Amino acid sequence: SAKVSGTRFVIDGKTGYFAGTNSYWIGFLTNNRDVDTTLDHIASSGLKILRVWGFNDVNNQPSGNTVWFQRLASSGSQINTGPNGLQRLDYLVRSAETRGIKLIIALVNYWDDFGGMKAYVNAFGGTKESWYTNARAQEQYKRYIQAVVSRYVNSPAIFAWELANEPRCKGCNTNVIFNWATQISDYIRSLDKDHLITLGDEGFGLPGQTTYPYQYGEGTDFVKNLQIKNLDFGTFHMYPGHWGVPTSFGPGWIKDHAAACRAAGKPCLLEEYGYESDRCNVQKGWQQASRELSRDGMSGDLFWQWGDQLSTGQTHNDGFTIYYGSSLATCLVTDHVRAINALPA
């Protein structure tokens, strides 16, 4: 149900460009109806891919019925397969199977939200930069990958396994993440031969311009990582307001990634993007630049992030949320999906 064909994706046997979104919170909901209604809204919007967090790491177990997936400690780490643990991810997967949504499931965070590499450093020592070569942290991270992947190997709702959300190794030789991603993607492939696998990086480090995002200072080399055999497609993210570059850098950023993916013979996915101001105009310009490259390396995009109305009220507005039913969703979801459906075949 989710494959690659040259520089394009194939979902439900259709080859082409797909739109999707991100919802880090959907895998942690404890109300099944809130998962179903959010997926119904995403599916009715014509979105096919949903990127979620498949991690929830803590150093101390939270109180009450708070959801957690893994507790990390120097000795005795535990993976939660209970009702407030991975059973919440199981429900998301089953609800996505029913509703025709393909999930990208990231397996650790580079950032501290939901624990991240920081929670592993707290348990296993070292620094965030040494996390990739920290044997005890990598041993537990692989145990966690096995615990998640083994549950959904036979699900048609997995778009791709994703190694990490936005992995960086600040100031590291770019071989650190390259070697790490090679060994972890080979590990995931041993557990699941058929689903796609991707890195989850921001896409820093590649030719095109001399601005900050093109530099190798965050430990990644986009072109180098596209050579990894068991990574099926390239991912890149786009946040000019955090990166000291204008919004007008967007089309070139997209073009430069699509050219690298084209040269590698793999699809590119613009996996997160957002801007806080003049949102419709700014982000519609980027969606057009991406759609225009649909036969030249780009094969989809996911905005960050979905917003909805749950039993617990409106979901969080982090300045990038696009709420279902809003005028901004008509601009960046309805009109986008209609423009994708109009692309030549």
Image (cartoon, rainbow, N blue to C red):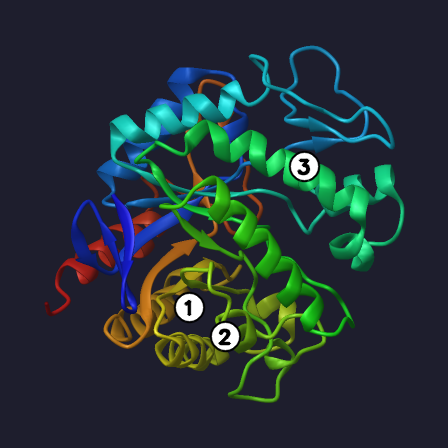
Amino acid marked by disc 1: Val
Q: Which residue is mark 3?
A: 114
Closest to the observer, 152 or 206: 152
At 42% from the left and 27% from the top, the residue drawn is 92
- From the top left corner, tell me how far across and down residue 74 is, in percent: 87, 32
Mark 3 residue element: loop
Q: CA distance from mark 2 to mark 3?
A: 29 Å
Amino acid marked by disc 3: Phe
Q: From what the image shows, is residue 38 above or below residue 275?
A: above
Count of marks, rendered view = 3
Left or right, residue 311 beside residue 114: left
Q: CA distance from mark 1 to mark 3?
A: 30 Å
Quick check: marks 1 and 2 in contact, CB under 8 Å? yes
- From the top left corner, tell me how far across and down residue 112 is, in percent: 73, 45
The numbered mark at residue 242 is none
Closest to the observer, 160 or 203: 160
Amino acid marked by disc 2: Thr
Instruction: Determine if residue 249 is in view.
Output: yes
Location of residue 100 by image quarter:
top left
Location of residue 306 by image quarter:
top left
Outermost residue on the front side: it is 190
At 44% from the left and 76% from the top, the residue drawn is 257
Q: Which residue is mark 2?
A: 247
Q: Earlier in the sequence, mark 2 or mark 3?
A: 3
The numbered mark at residue 282 is 1
